[PDB]
Length: 294
Ligand SMILES: N[C@@H](CCC(=O)N[C@@H](CS)C(=O)NCC(=O)O)C(=O)O
Image (cartoon, rainbow, N blue to C red):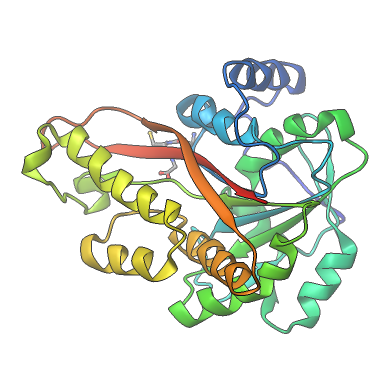
């Protein structure tokens, strides 16, 4: 049995040198003023750090490392035909900063729901959408580096009913101030290379239409409304890569509202990998945001 998941995208999606990566993350985090501490959930991108690291800092700066003790990371599956969610087979997730330990107690509880499959080590290491949050998490939590655990969850192509069921399942954990939910997603992938060319001419340039479409989705997320978000996906089919983890989060939020809790979500930074101006251009969008529970 292999006990460690190697940092299989280090050096290609982010800097492999621990000390240099540490300084790069520190630099991006220093440019952000914390406004939403202590975040109970964040939405953050999963592209290479050269493209999205500055944006992701706006989410990670909202984590209060003196409060958060367990960090769920829900990332969408890119390679495998997964219809449910999957849990890791290893005990430790490596990063160039320091290695992260999976919460064995919660992993046992989750497994006993019967709702999860077990992803192989090969599946685990092939996916990047969880790994891209490990260095940032390690950096955000370094002042308490030996006092927190992670709960990695691979999120497949969930049906609406599975988004509802997993949302209700995770809601009991979302209600605990010691827990943090990292919801991994990029926003619009625009261009012929993505077979996506939706364009609202009332917005002007293509990149402004992309910004408007993304921000329609971001505003719906801020309305805490999973049905509205599903309807928006059905209407425009925006290529939001973590739409299923987001659907899980929104259903968890509505479950907590039914239990009498009150919540607020705010997006804090929006960016595009480039600015599309003609039909042959392509770009990927990034958005960072935080959920506050009082
Ligand atoms: N170096 C990595 C990452 C490259 C990368 O991050 N590309 C951007 C687009 S310029 C991106 O957004 N990737 C994640 C996504 O498409 O959602 C690779 O070769 O795939």
